[PDB]
Amino acid sequence: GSADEELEALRRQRLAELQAKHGDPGDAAQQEAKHREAEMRNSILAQVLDQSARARLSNLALVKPEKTKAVENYLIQMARYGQLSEKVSEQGLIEILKKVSQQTEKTTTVKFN
């Protein structure tokens, strides 16, 4: 088993270990870095919030992005708990949104953004 994989690995090893750099540690790398910042946040949100929840989040950002910022942040926290076996549905996002509407997410812990 995995013979084709380990075979391909030898070829890929030459490719991977080579490490194609672009020469400079700037410009594209800066945008790349910033993209990775978003990517990590976007990926967890896209996996935790299903399509429906994203669409609702988008419309929420349309009406008042202030709270969007709070719930986006909140979902990042919730995702960091690794408790998302299931998708957060629209109703779930709305339940969260309800408690965060004024301000109820500032827990006594230093949470990241």
Image (cartoon, rainbow, N blue to C red):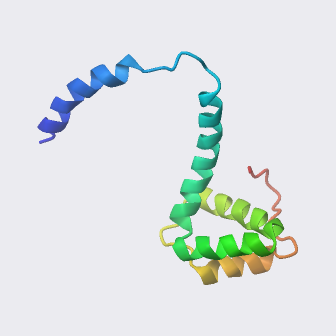
Instruction: Give the quadrant of residue 103.
Output: bottom right
Position in image of residue 53 (x %, y %): 59, 74
Which of 36/1 is in front?
36
Which of 33/113 is in front?
33
In the rendered image, the residue lying farthest to the bottom is 91
Q: Is residue 94 left or right of residue 2?
A: right
Residue 83: tell me if it is visible: no
Which of 74/57 is in front?
57
Q: Is residue 44 left or right of residue 104?
A: left
Instruction: Give the quadrant of residue 96.
Output: bottom right
Above-or-below relation of 19 to 87: above
Above-or-below relation of 106 to 9: below
Q: Residue at 72% of width from left, 59% of height from top? A: 73
Q: Residue at 61% of width from left, 56% of height from top? A: 80
Position in image of residue 9 (x %, y %): 23, 29
Instruction: Give the quadrant of residue 19.
Output: top left
Q: Residue at 77% of width from left, 62% of height from top? A: 69
Q: Quadrant of the N terminus?
A: top left
In the rendered image, the residue lying farthest to the right is 102
Q: Residue at 52% of width from left, 72% of height from top? A: 51
Q: Is residue 17 left or right of residue 111?
A: left
Position in image of residue 63 (x %, y %): 79, 75
Position in image of residue 2 (x %, y %): 16, 40
- The mark total stands at 0
Residue 4: tell me if it is visible: yes
